[PDB]
Image (cartoon, rainbow over all chains, first blue to last red; front, side, top):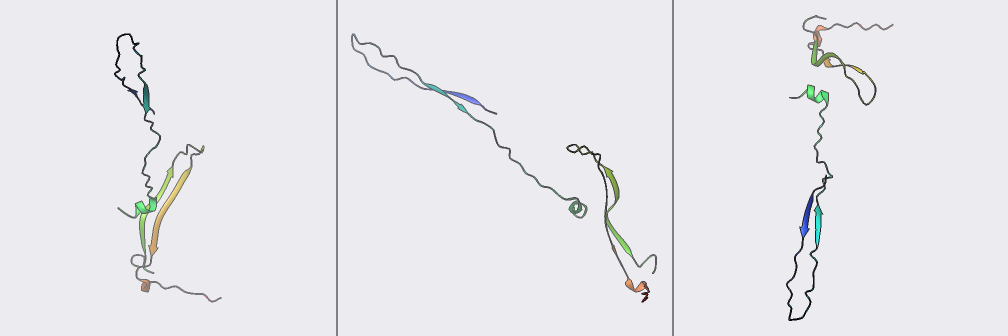
Length: 55
Length: 53
């Protein structure tokens, strides 16, 4: 009943000068879900007598 | 009365005996139904006799 689509983020450009360490950055992610849980319906009962006395 | 013009039997569902298997309840239930209506066309042709004890 579920359905999965992954998501992903982006990194950011950073500057550096001579002897400066390159700071590592994470790239976050996640997931998304779509869950079917409801049943749409139409329920129309016709009695026998009304059937026998109407087209 | 007259046996041709004194009565009428309007029928929408004639006599019907039907057997259907109930599954939720263990049962070979038998139905037997009939829907109709009787009316007295031309009541002037009928002659009842009341009996007053």
